Length: 224
Length: 223
Ligand SMILES: [Mg+2]
Ligand SMILES: [Mg+2]
Ligand code: NA
Ligand code: NA
Image 1 (cartoon, rainbow over the protein chains, first blue to last red):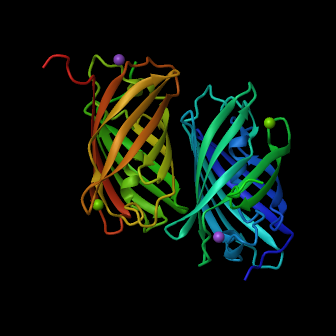
Image 2: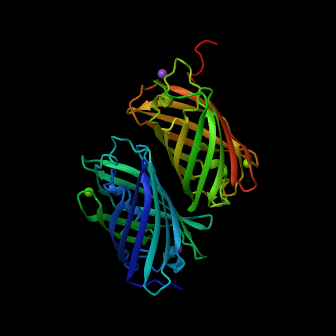
Image 3: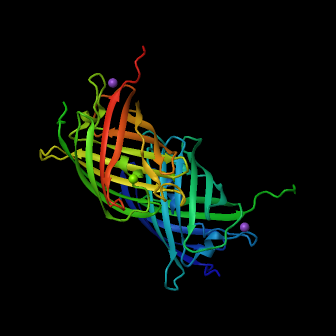
């Protein structure tokens, strides 16, 4: 039985370090689990102004916000109220690499709210690279590949940051999703994503995000 | 001018998380910079007993402890008293991966002591893997390849953990060393390492380490 509702709140707190630079970011937002859309307003409370591209942090700021068709098992909505946690490695093509974790649960009060405890760490970003030079524009849309492995769910996605000077900067995502209770496991499937920074101040101490995500089973066998 | 001396103290504090499990470890030790040897006694003060193999943490607990030949530029000893920091990615063959950083400096009270601030994070370690099942025996010796890249020093090394059931579990290290001041840069070279846990209690809440390291220029051209 699912306890998810159409309108739910989001509370997040991220603590981390990139190339040794420590920072803390908090935020509040809301989302529509069944429509696969969400928003969050972020505020850098420690470590600002960040010396690296804020874009590397955005996907860390919940697959429960995905419109899942009836035919596909929803690993995430089943996991609540207890919730689930995820672990992720984000390997950039120039050697830079980030690891992040998020422990998600719903508040015990009927406030329909998700609480997110996030840790984010990145290292080996070249001083003259697009991340430390803040030359990123946005993440392109993507299609995450979902598959079960040893009783848990994995999601791998080829990501790409559009650069200011044109061209792309690739990053390979490897995520492991772990429900806090036994839930039905889904067959191999996909999750399309579109996420962007809808607003931000000069130094990105204030950032607004938006994401739209939908699950599917890939292209039909027959054309048209 | 180097301010390094033959006998120096070591103080370390590591804060981290592996597969979401938080922990804090502190330690005290000593080393001989010129002989390339060092020891450290570690104590898990938070998060114990650790659910993962302690071996994944040991290389995080200073390349200043390497016997460098006269003919090879020593990037590390030159950096003090200011010091240097390092960043490292440790990619295991089964997908597990760890990142760590260490900010190293010398105390300014004349106590000949290195202070180390370490952050360690690991994710994607399979529940049935040797790390989460604590089936590791030790790290084999190694030879780290040192090369300059964009004004800083990189060190890459093929590492391997001997497993209890026999066989090895490989990990590729990619480290970036950054001096806090301008120092002479070295030519491509190598650093041989031998590190081991010389003592530990049942759950590894108490662990003693030892490392021996020496730099060199590789095999001579002639046999
Ligand atoms: Mg922008
Ligand atoms: Mg042992
Ligand atoms: Na399914
Ligand atoms: Na040299």
